[PDB]
Length: 157
Ligand SMILES: Nc1nc2c(ncn2[C@@H]2O[C@H](COP(=O)(O)OP(=O)(O)O)[C@@H](O)[C@H]2O)c(=O)[nH]1
Ligand SMILES: [Mg+2]
Ligand code: NA
Image 1 (cartoon, helix red, strand yellow):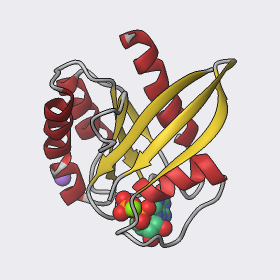
Image 2: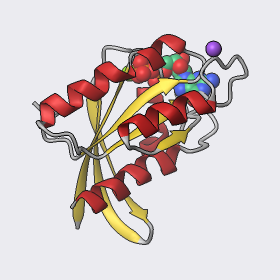
Image 3: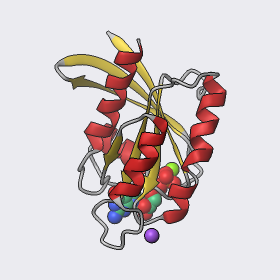
């Protein structure tokens, strides 16, 4: 079966771990030690295809990543501001401009929003990447974010 190595990056507190655990374990974590960096697997079906996802939740495996989720939180302007740092890291570690990537705006369940959809869509367009709005709490968008990334890897191959 086809394996996809995915890496989740972004500022502390955006929901990288919550997004990962919701995908893998089907539950929402209200707190998750921010120093734990681990890799997590789930065999899933994406568009009818069975595949293995190896997901590195960051906090010697970044460089082997085939696609990256760049996460910010929609009530965390600072995390949005930091996205360019993580995009550039990824370019450098892959030595490429064309790396499969998805911009994820998480915590969409929260009303105290400060990054609007247009802002984020504009950033995504400046990188040529999809933008997906998620909630790790509700599950909105979660599969779509990871599965879109897999679809970007599929195209890239
Ligand atoms: N309301 C809400 N809280 C979230 C969401 N995702 C994460 N959180 C919370 O935000 C905090 C940080 O999440 P965490 O996954 O540890 O962020 P990380 O540092 O990026 O791994 C925790 O208290 C999570 O419960 C979400 O979509 N909605
Ligand atoms: Mg974490
Ligand atoms: Na503003």
